[PDB]
Image: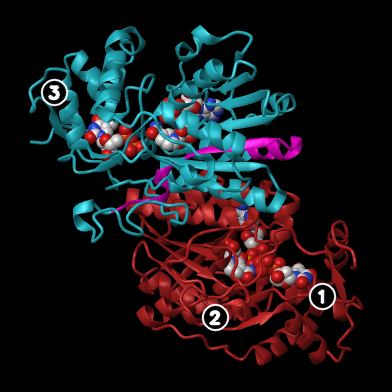
Chain colours: A cyan, B red
Amino acid sequence: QFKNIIVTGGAGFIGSNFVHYVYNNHPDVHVTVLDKLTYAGNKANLEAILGDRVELVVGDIADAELVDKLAAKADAIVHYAAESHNDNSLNDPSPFIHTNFIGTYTLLEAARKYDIRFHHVSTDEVYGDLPLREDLPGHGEGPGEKFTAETNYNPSSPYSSTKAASDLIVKAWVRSFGVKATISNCSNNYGPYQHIEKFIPRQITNILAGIKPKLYGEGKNVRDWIHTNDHSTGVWAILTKGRMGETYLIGADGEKNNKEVLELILEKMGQPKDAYDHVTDRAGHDLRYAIDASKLRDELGWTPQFTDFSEGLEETIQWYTDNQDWWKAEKEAVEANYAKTQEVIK
Amino acid sequence: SQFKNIIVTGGAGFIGSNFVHYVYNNHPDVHVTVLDKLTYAGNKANLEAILGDRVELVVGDIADAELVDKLAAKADAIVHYAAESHNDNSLNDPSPFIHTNFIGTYTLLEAARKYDIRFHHVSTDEVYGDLPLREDLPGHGEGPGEKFTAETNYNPSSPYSSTKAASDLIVKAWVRSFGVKATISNCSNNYGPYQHIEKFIPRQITNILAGIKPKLYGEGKNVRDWIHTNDHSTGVWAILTKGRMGETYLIGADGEKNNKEVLELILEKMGQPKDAYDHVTDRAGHDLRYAIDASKLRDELGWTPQFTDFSEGLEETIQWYTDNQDWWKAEKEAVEANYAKTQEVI
Ligand SMILES: NC(=O)c1ccc[n+]([C@@H]2O[C@H](COP(=O)([O-])OP(=O)(O)OC[C@H]3O[C@@H](n4cnc5c(N)ncnc54)[C@H](O)[C@@H]3O)[C@@H](O)[C@H]2O)c1
Ligand SMILES: NC(=O)c1ccc[n+]([C@@H]2O[C@H](COP(=O)([O-])OP(=O)(O)OC[C@H]3O[C@@H](n4cnc5c(N)ncnc54)[C@H](O)[C@@H]3O)[C@@H](O)[C@H]2O)c1
Ligand SMILES: Cc1cn([C@H]2C[C@H](O)[C@@H](COP(=O)(O)OP(=O)(O)O)O2)c(=O)[nH]c1=O
Ligand SMILES: Cc1cn([C@H]2C[C@H](O)[C@@H](COP(=O)(O)OP(=O)(O)O)O2)c(=O)[nH]c1=O
């Protein structure tokens, strides 16, 4: 029900995947991507589909003058733009404060001015940490053993804290000014086009480059994995059918500890089960994340389609193997940056 | 008295100036450096009497990283009161709230991290949102969740409360991620000497003294938990010197009252008819009832409020504004004029 939408952060991982989704399934919609092209922005993620349906505008979401020019011609804003890596936020929180909070505020004021639709894309990390299933009476199935729309905010890092802060002002702008906004908090995404600084693609590409995979500590931490294609359909459902002012949780019930994920990657790529390095653990590292997506399923009828992790991972490994020119120019620089704060445990 | 050289941000304001006076009179071994921007709310007269070898006033912005670094380099603690504190102003122009409440707190946190010094964040009960009236609660206000506690979910309604809540979140993340030595306090509505005339109680008192009729938003059923600024001061001191690192403490004196009954008591004490006031346009997103359970502070730190008699406290406050008319007479006209731009008798 929208014809001219702005997608911020559309040259990144999750955002570019959403743009591809629109280009393929809703050809009647025009998309204007607003992206600053930081270390994480890549024109290659959109180059093949740029045209009458999709255009790219290079700029900052904190640039009020530019945002005003674009907002005056749109009927909706889908907001993905952000500094998204915890490890980078621990080394230098500056850009997180700027982009995640000030950037969201700038966009909210534009939505208010032109009275248009706004969907805020956020993360499950705003809720903090959860204990491992082995230490819970309900084994992870009981009340409060998973995140729900009623869970309190309790972020652990500069990244999750600035995202949570942005969630708070979006909701305040709805109650105070009647902005037409909705919010989504999603679990860990994986799939094609994810930057190699992130867990899954870092291990896959290190192996392809003849470098040892890296595991933080002993790998006890748990993440709830969801394929980006399912994140895309969830956001589209909320954008077009959601209730104004509501928050929806997106997840596919795919909890796994880092150790088992790395072991699956090694096995699929024909490597020995112990061919990896244990490395310096992350400060304030979150233990377990888990999402209860009952609300979105019940109210909007959304159902994830990529629930077979083994197959999804197999296809992801093949994509990075078939598109080595997409990441090879960044491998040395990313690993060198990590070497400044991480070393092999022994 | 473990801290000998402290910085008090926003010390030229209402609550902050009362805290500086408290330190001057009860902890003579402490030197105080006040950092205040002197906005419409800052007033040098609130500190004049005690300025000298023991208390210094430095005019500046908490977002000025260079100035903050210079002052932090010679301090052993920072007590943070600086902020844009009025909901009504935040609804008219959120800009200064974004700047001061969030960016300002971030700047101070980085300075505390660099020099590894104590940091106490002064916050509000409004970060928790709103509560139903006691007559509409199954436990009449005495049951679980019928009052705010340290476990209550954040759910701010306005630009003011959401920016304050946002600052609370990054303070907690800096503790978990970087080991910053911070504590947080969330307090109920303060009243007493030196409060700006834009606030509820002082506005009604001074309006009567100036020949202007009091103003009540709607029917005045909204409820607030009143505490005398002197008890807020001793509460912050207990948390600063004995509080557990990383913990949040709620400050309150169990004094819930509805706006209507508070205004009537004022009219009565100042010899005015019970109907000598006007009903005016209600506040957008206006919060219903606020209530604080201060058990944690009382039980764990041994703190107890001394001004539990509201009638007596209010009497002394009316007397203060009556004996110090030169302190506010010059601002009366401007404040009421600003209000007239959005408020009309109904
Ligand atoms: N990675 C995940 O698993 C995940 C899971 C849930 C929610 N989220 C959220 O999804 C969104 C997108 O995540 P991602 O993994 O695709 O991130 P990403 O790192 O892959 O891409 C971020 C993108 O935003 C752009 N950007 C950064 N600052 C900008 C600014 N000031 N103005 C304009 N563009 C700017 C970058 O150029 C880049 O293209 C974020 O808001 C993130 O918090 C991420
Ligand atoms: N008034 C209340 O009932 C109340 C209740 C609970 C919590 N609080 C909190 O208590 C603190 C103080 O409240 P208040 O009523 O005394 O406010 P106030 O309006 O009386 O004073 C604010 C002070 O901060 C200064 N200031 C504003 N922006 C600044 C900046 N960028 N740099 C430096 N100084 C700046 C102003 O000049 C002023 O002296 C706030 O953080 C507020 O959120 C207030
Ligand atoms: C980047 C990276 C992450 N990890 C871990 C840390 C996290 O528990 C998990 C995913 O990390 P990451 O991809 O950074 O995502 P997020 O912090 O948002 O969940 O993988 C490793 O073990 N090794 C690595 O090289
Ligand atoms: C300033 C003012 C406030 N009020 C009400 C609104 C609030 O419920 C209450 C206190 O308002 P206020 O002093 O602005 O404090 P806060 O919003 O931080 O609680 O008094 C009036 O009825 N009339 C007025 O003129």
What segment carries the magenta color? A106-130
Callout 1: helix, strand or loop?
helix
Determine the chain carrying the residue at label 1: B
- Horizontally, is A336 left or right of A264 in the view? right
Three-letter code for the amino acid on which mark 2 is drawn: Gly
Three-letter code for the amino acid on which mark 1 is drawn: Asp
CB atoms of marks 2 and 3 within 8 Å:
no
Mark 1 — residue?
B326
Mark 3 — residue?
A267
Q: Quadrant of residue A259?
A: top left
Q: Relative to residue A320, is residue A18 depicted above or below?
A: below
Q: x, y (%) of residue A66?
A: 68, 25
Determine the chain carrying the residue at label 3: A
| Residue occupying the point 55% across, 83% down | B254
| Residue occupying the point 46% across, 76% down | B144
Can residue A200 be seen here? The reply is yes
Q: Using a 10 Å C-alpha cutoff, classify the residue at mark 2 as few (fewer than 14 neighbours), some (14 to 19) or many (20 or more).
A: some
Q: Relative to residue B310, is residue B236 depicted above or below?
A: above
Determine the chain carrying the residue at label 2: B
Q: Quadrant of ligand 2?
A: bottom right
